[PDB]
Image (tube, coloured by chain):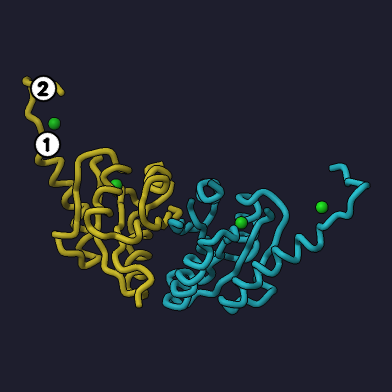
Chain colours: A cyan, B yellow
Amino acid sequence: MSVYHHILLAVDFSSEDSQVVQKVRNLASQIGARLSLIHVLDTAIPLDTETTYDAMLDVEKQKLSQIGNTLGIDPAHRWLVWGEPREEIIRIAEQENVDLIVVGSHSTANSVLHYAKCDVLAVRL
Amino acid sequence: MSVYHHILLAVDFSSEDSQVVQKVRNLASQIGARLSLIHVLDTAIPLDTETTYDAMLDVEKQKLSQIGNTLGIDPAHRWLVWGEPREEIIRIAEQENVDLIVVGSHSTANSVLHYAKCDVLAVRL
Ligand SMILES: [Cl-]
Ligand SMILES: [Cl-]
Ligand SMILES: [Cl-]
Ligand SMILES: [Cl-]
């Protein structure tokens, strides 16, 4: 039986994403685990200018989707959430029955690591 | 090909070792990696009493060997070293061409993680 069943990858959209993506794909396939994906984004509204929240979200959505598409993850298992990375990472992991969180170091990594209720894989970038 | 080739397990000889041992055995076997093992021990000599350095080392050696024997690791790949855990863990990993260090949390974990030149798997105990 599989040593981990459900691996959550956290990506930050750096140029080094691709190393981690292929590694995590090889990982999950060799051990038989399913993958989910999350990226954490990353008060006065300016009145003299057009806001670009939706366009900015679309860029993020595309980057998430580049990665999601490579990994064959259903959009239902791709997460783009507002908030503090550590907290949001850990809340999705709990909610979604993850048993391995994967993060890159380069922080967020060290905070997820100190508060996660499951194993954490920190991948050197 | 194997996502990791050489996994170094670090054990501290707590009652929770066995969970980590079987997990790491299942891990390495599913991905095709070889295992090494390390435990880091863990100025005036008393003149009125017998010292027990050798007996104390034998106890540690037995505990290392319980774990090593389970995992089928040659004694050549089992390490019982004097020193600061973080430093010694990282020095063996470098020396021995490790590409995944495994540690339990419960520290040492967070220090190995902040200075390791390879991926680190932190296993919740
Ligand atoms: Cl993130
Ligand atoms: Cl805006
Ligand atoms: Cl140790
Ligand atoms: Cl002594």
Determine which of the numbered discs, if any, sits on residue A11 in the image. Answer: none
- Residue B67 against residue A73 in the figure, above or below: above
Mark drawn on residue B46: 2
Residue B16 in view (yes/no)? no
Q: Is residue B72 above or below residue B51?
A: below
Q: Which residue is mark 1?
A: B53
Element type at marker 1? helix
**Mark 2 surroundings: few (<14), some (14-19) or many (≥20) residues within 10 A:** few
Q: Secondary structure at mark 2?
A: loop
Q: Using the image, determine if residue A84 lies above or below residue B2.
A: above
Between the residue at mark 2 and the residue at mark 1, the CA separation in whole angstroms equals: 12 Å
Pinpoint residue B105: horizontal percent, then vertical percent.
42, 49
User: How many discs appear?
Assistant: 2
Q: Name the residue furthest front.
A: A48
Ligand 4 closer than 8 Å to the CB at disc 1?
yes
Residue A43: x and y in percent read 84, 42
The residue type indicated by label 2 comes to Pro
Instruction: Return the chain for callout 1.
Output: B
Query: Quick check: B71 left or right of B120?
Result: left
Q: Which quadrant of the figure has residue A26?
A: bottom left
Whether the residue under disc 2 has CB within 8 Å of ligand 4:
yes
**Image quadrant where one finds the N terminus of chain A:** bottom left
Residue closer to the observer: A19 or B41: A19
- Ligand 4's image quarter is top left
In the figure, is residue A6 to the left or right of B72? right
Mark 1 is on which residue type?
A: Tyr
Rendering coords of residue A102 (x, y %): 51, 61
Residue sticking out furthest to the right? A47
Residue B12 rendering spot, x and y as whole percentages: 31, 48
